[PDB]
Image: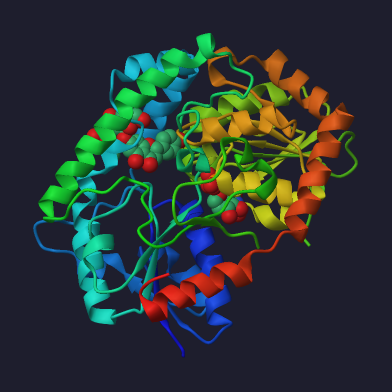
Length: 419
Ligand SMILES: C[C@@H]1O[C@@H](O[C@H]2[C@H](Oc3cc(O)c4c(c3)O[C@H](c3ccc(O)cc3)CC4=O)O[C@H](CO)[C@@H](O)[C@@H]2O)[C@H](O)[C@H](O)[C@H]1O
Ligand SMILES: O=c1ccn([C@@H]2O[C@H](COP(=O)(O)OP(=O)(O)O)[C@@H](O)[C@H]2O)c(=O)[nH]1
């Protein structure tokens, strides 16, 4: 009856959360939880009572495990300079048939070898994995494997291409090109996946195929009901911060600013956003990121490298975000309107979904001005319809619950090896 359940995920701290939440639900039903990842996450995994397995302990000698987190600042700075210079359309034209994240595929060989060895050693009854793309080990190991998805799920539908930030309001003439480019770039992702799968002698699958079951986490009221149903076997899983003294005795609303764990490594991005907010008549709490001591703060601001974001969000009036999925769900669960300044990949889809459903505004780096940021703040704080829309979504998120259904499917698959 007690199952052995093994999780793993990509390097993003965001890619941990769905996995951690699903693991907590299964541990409460008496299952043994294992989580394979990097040492930096041992503390959170062991605090949850899951057994921590270090990917680094299982590397094949000639395929060292690529750890992308420490170098992310270099990659993130290149992405920032493209976003500040180019329109979304120009970004795709300049990409010239290269894909947003296919660059990561070749380097994934070491992690695949490690997971092969980990699943052979620990012999779990089922595995769950939150990746950007399927990996060969998911089709070679002796147990069922559930892909877990936390990125914007438009890629699970037959609609507008993923990673473009297409609007529901874009006419066919306006989008037909950016869409064609996105299609040529899907072929580069397939080509790189074909080389990774060939290396391991595994027949290639679609990058987001769910063989028996896939679990995606996205706000129900934001999901793409207008595109019909997600891909086969995918199911949606619906589940006191102390204010600094510096910001007391000061007028205006309280605003949280975060460009997320990864993009915040780019000090130039936060500096570009903060400078004009010195003149906004409100109070700002800032997640300053790992280089945060290099970031200048003004008299109306307080910040630290890593904020207790979930404790803070109920106390704020507005969330200035990069539009990452974890930040989107946390902000809307707390009932706070968003200004999304997207930085990379699925953040463009989330930013446009916020604008399209009246939950906030999208502000692009390529046409950014201080005047426009300050005006976005005043507009959203005073927009009774946006504040009503956000309140309605937060209520729906508090009520919606698919846990029993999804846990039953995981347990059924773990025991029967079929659904
Ligand atoms: C994995 C990387 O692959 C190449 O590089 C490409 C780069 O590859 C990635 C692959 C990824 O999986 C990610 C990435 C870049 O950056 C993402 C990112 C994260 C945070 C940000 O603020 C901005 C961007 C994170 C991610 O998952 O993609 C660019 C287009 O989006 C291309 O122009 C780059 O040739 C290049 O070989 C890099 O040296 C190598 O580290
Ligand atoms: O200063 C910070 C930055 C991030 N996070 C948490 O780290 C996770 C990932 O945040 P990020 O914005 O990087 O994720 P994304 O929105 O891109 O998915 C979430 O649970 C956030 O609440 C946090 O607590 N404090």
